[PDB]
Amino acid sequence: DISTEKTVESLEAIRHRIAQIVQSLTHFLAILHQSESLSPWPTIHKNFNILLSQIHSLSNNLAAHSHTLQTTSIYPSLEFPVKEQEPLLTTLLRTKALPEVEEWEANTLQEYEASISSQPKKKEANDAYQKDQLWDQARIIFMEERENYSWFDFVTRRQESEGEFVSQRQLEIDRATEEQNANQMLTDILSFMKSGKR
Amino acid sequence: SDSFQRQLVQRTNTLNSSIDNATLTILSRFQDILDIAINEGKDKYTVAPEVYQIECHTVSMVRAVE
Amino acid sequence: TSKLYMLSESPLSTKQILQTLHALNMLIRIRLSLYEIIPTPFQHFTIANGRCTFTVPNEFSVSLTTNSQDPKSTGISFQWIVVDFQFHLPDFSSTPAKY
Amino acid sequence: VDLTSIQWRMPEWVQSMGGLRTENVLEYFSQSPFYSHKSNNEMLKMQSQFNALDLGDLNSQLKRLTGIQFVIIHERPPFLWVIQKQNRLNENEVKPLTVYFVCNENIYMAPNAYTLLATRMLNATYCFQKALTKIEKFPQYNPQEGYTYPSPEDFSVVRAFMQSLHSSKEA
Amino acid sequence: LKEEDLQKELQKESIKTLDSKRNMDSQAYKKELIEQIMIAQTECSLALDMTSLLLSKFKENSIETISPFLKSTVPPSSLQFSRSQPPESKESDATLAKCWKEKSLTSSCKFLFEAKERLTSVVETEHEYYTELVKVKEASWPLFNSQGSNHLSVQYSCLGGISLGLGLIRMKP
Amino acid sequence: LLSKVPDDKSRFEIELEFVQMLSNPWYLNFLAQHKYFEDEAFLQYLEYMEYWREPEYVKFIIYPTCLHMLTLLKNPQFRNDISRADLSKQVNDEIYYEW
Amino acid sequence: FSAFPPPPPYYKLFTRENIEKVISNMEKEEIESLAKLFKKPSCLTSGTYQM
């Protein structure tokens, strides 16, 4: 029964995540409906982004509890039997893929069939592994290369760092002190005019 | 109201804020495409969100450039 | 549901559509001569090519000028049983164009 | 043949025997693609030829036997029954390999939570990718005009019309 | 439609593969979008409801998460779950996944190419317009951004007089 | 671009049966849900189905409906509405009544 | 829950590109000949009745 309660807390977590994404999707729907003309690309795009963050969190939860979720299986019984007469159950627990998805899959598999027309299959899997390796290498060298540069400076490339140096805050401090001393010059000349202090 | 110099520095800090924000989203988006480009775990259900993410990130990159 | 979603064959005989137009104009004459109510400013009308046309002097670089002819099937002759009324269909000319 | 998406039943069989019973639920199962003919219940059916039996005998001989077995997990007489494809290598301990669903003279797969939630997520994803791919090509960007998707005098012309209309409506 | 034009066309007509071969609204794109997100929302809402039913058998947390229509229609503690064995993985399924990601990357890099090309056209026109503005202010005519915040306006009434008149430069493309 | 793998006799047996499928409204509904109407290749294949109206060929077809169905499907708005379940039932019921 | 057979794969074959390639074939007068063999409707006279 320990496995059962672990699956309980797990599916609790996924329930919370899917709840939040329902709320975000309904919000999106509302903003869409709010204006008769379609909404401005900046805002809709922003909402696509939040949607992405939600679905990413969900996929992480599912892969983390993937073992405990594929061992467990769901059948209705006992208390649903009062409403058991209805086909709502079959529609609710159905795991048929969407028709668009289903076709999609079929088409992509046909494409693989053109590819096998091109070449033999045994060679394909090792090449695939080698590529995944490639991508991981590209990732780490990009991290290094990026950490190498400097970003939030004014004209301060690597090359320009060798060249010269430019300071915004020093300019600002400079102008500030110049204006303050200039003001003291003012107050001094004003007291001179009023009553000689030359 | 704010000083004249306050106005100037206000502006530049604004233009920066906006501009390092845009560059930083270019970097970070490309980075995260890369983080997602490997297909080793290859749970087809995980691969499909990944595809969405890829599309959404590239578009976010062009957005930043604009 | 067939008749609403039905669609005719794509050929339209252009000699036919002229003859439709003739019979249509002619049929607006029928209607109008025995249409019950004309407003007196409308008393002069031209049965145009395809169209009924109506002119009343006006400003803003145009005359108040409307063109009517109609698509309701049921009435076409029943338009005369319905001397009271009719679907008519317009096409009015001013100096603007889109609006 | 994918066994999980599909929904099967044989009302002809049910009417042939008559009403829906415990034992007839297991026979009905025997007719379904879900049942496997190498099953232990099938080996028992082969061993006895047109004689009476008993149900307590059925479970007790299921445990006595070692291999793939189909038993009743929960039973509700009016409409629905619950079957599982449990595999016991030894008695008193069983590893359930599949669960199976019976409802209104219908047999169903009753699948694993992971595949349900996963497929759901996959649908949602697909909707997203399609909508975004349709939108992304459309909008236009000019840098001075902004983002575009492909006068007050005229507005006053409209006001004149709507007011004319309101007048005619009131009349 | 004119009778003379038509008598000309029809008079011109009197002069005259077995397979038949034949070859949008912002509101329309809008409809497509809301359609798609709506189908997503109905799918996710379904999953939400089902999970909520089960957990509501085992927690307060999911009487909340289940929809009011569904909780009104069906008694709580309805669904069940038992340990079972996960299904055999399909070779076609994984080869599918890999095919999907590869196509995804190629799609992305192509999109970056074309986006670069269109933005280069954009920057080209921009460069044109601004070289002409530079030409203008090189002649010491003041200019101010227009009220619409698109383009810029020159102050032709800058030599003198009472009224102040300014007008925006636009590219007739 | 996989090489075509068809059979001569078999594909006229098959194209006959496919026309028959087109007679069924529920098959049209599923077809629309699967967004087969999104593909232009499909629509050209429909015109290829026009060969089945020819007398020697139509002499073979069993269910007349398909022919009508085919002309019905030439309107695209009809295609999106046979995606709809309600209209689907309307069509089925309309045959059922004629029958 | 209910399902029917998909149409022939060669529906998926059609493109207006290959169509234009076969009208170019017509203009000239392997692949093209296979396309026109595909486009003819060769009816049958006698001998087959089953589904």
Image (spheres, rainbow, N blue to C red):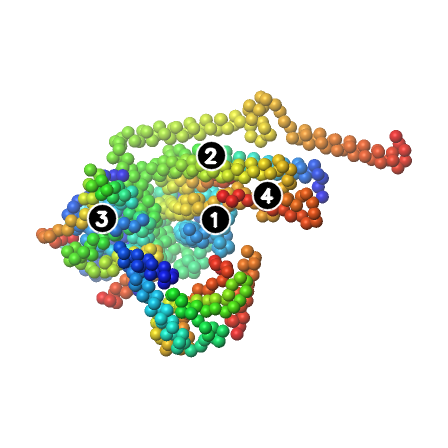
Residue linked to disc 3: E17
4 vs 2, front mark: 4
Q: Which numbered tag is attached to residue E152?
A: 4
Quadrant in the rendering for residue E4: bottom left
Q: Is D169 on the left-hand or right-hand side of E164?
A: left
Element type where label 1 sits in the image: loop
Of D95 and D12, the residue lying toward us: D12
Q: Is E132 on the left-hand or right-hand side of A108?
A: right
Mark-to-mark CA distance, 3 and 2? 51 Å
Outermost top residue: A162
Q: Residue at image x 36%, y 63%?
A: E3
The 10 Å Cα crowd at callout 2, few under 14, some 14 to 19, many 20 or more, is some
Mark 1 and mark 2 on one chain: no
Mark 1 and mark 4 on one chain: no
Where residue A83 appears, as percent x and y from the top left, is 36, 60
Element type where label 4 sits in the image: strand
Where residue D165 appears, as percent x and y from the top left, is 52, 68
Residue linked to disc 2: B30
Q: Chain of mark 3?
A: E
3 vs 2, front mark: 3
- Specify the amino acid type for callout 3: Thr
The 10 Å Cα crowd at callout 1, few under 14, some 14 to 19, many 20 or more, is some
Mark-to-mark CA distance, 1 and 2? 27 Å
Mark-to-mark CA distance, 4 and 2? 35 Å
Q: Residue at image x 56%, y 38%?
A: E132
Residue linked to disc 1: D149
3 vs 1, front mark: 3
